[PDB]
Figure 1 (cartoon, rainbow, N blue to C red):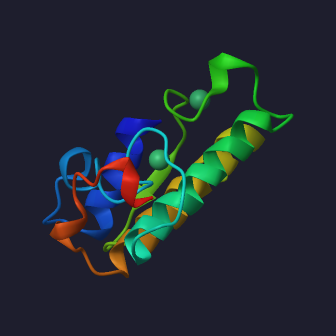
Figure 2 (cartoon, rainbow, N blue to C red; figure 1 turned 30 degrees about the horizontal axis):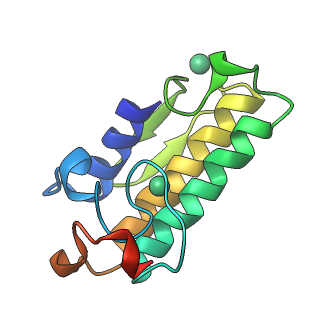
Length: 123
Ligand SMILES: [Ca+2]
Ligand SMILES: [Ca+2]
């Protein structure tokens, strides 16, 4: 679930404010997204967006009910390291890995504040 993805990002980047820092950034960081990613962070979000789309089409995920935004799963934060629990069902495990991969990706790319609030004409 979204609030859990927030926790994952905090796990990897303690000094960050997820819902603020990684929203309205580039062409993909935020609700929706299309076009050409402006930098590596934007590419992280593009990959995450595609991952969420796959989850919604996944056979193991029930129609709304198991959507990526509100479907809670089990995960752990150990020394700034994320772990998806083997207690998760197939649907939850897929979503948890979508988030885990993105959290890690965010932590390995530079943050360029000049890419915030870009108009669609730049995508
Ligand atoms: Ca997006
Ligand atoms: Ca669940």
